[PDB]
Amino acid sequence: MTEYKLVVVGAGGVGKSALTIQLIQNHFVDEYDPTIEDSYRKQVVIDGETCLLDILDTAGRDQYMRTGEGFLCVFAINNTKSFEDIHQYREQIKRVKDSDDVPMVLVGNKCDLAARTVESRQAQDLARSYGIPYIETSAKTRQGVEDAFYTLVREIRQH
Ligand SMILES: Nc1nc2c(ncn2[C@@H]2O[C@H](COP(=O)(O)OP(=O)(O)NP(=O)(O)O)[C@@H](O)[C@H]2O)c(=O)[nH]1
Ligand SMILES: [Mg+2]
Image (cartoon, rainbow, N blue to C red; front, side, top):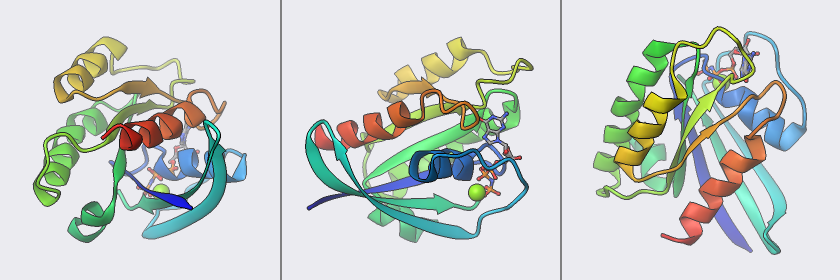
């Protein structure tokens, strides 16, 4: 079956693992557990198409960026530093893949938190400048999780 090689990147602690575990294991990991490198393979049905999601959950590079087909670039809405770091991930991915239009979704996670420091407007404008979608998520409530991953799969389909 069709396989989608997804890679989740972003600053340490923004919720890359929490988002992935929510999608695949249907629960919120509310504990400290830094990632080195974890892989998740799951058969799913997206828009009627049977496919395999091969998700690489990374640590907060060139090798995995090269094989990845789509990227979720994640930052946390209560961590301005993580938002400012997005540019560096974006540039490295573009360089390694020799492409300025790589399937990608900008993800603003932890949207359940009231202590926001990154305005949705600034993230939206950045995404617009990259020509990619901006989606806010909460690995805690599961809001926007399937949306983020499925949108990424669709971006790959339309590449
Ligand atoms: N309130 C809230 N907390 C979240 C959310 N996503 C993750 N967290 C919390 O943020 C912390 C770090 O999440 P984690 O998934 O481990 O982040 P990571 O990006 O995978 N870290 P690392 O790069 O080191 O692998 C955890 O305490 C986790 O519960 C979210 O949407 N909302
Ligand atoms: Mg992690």
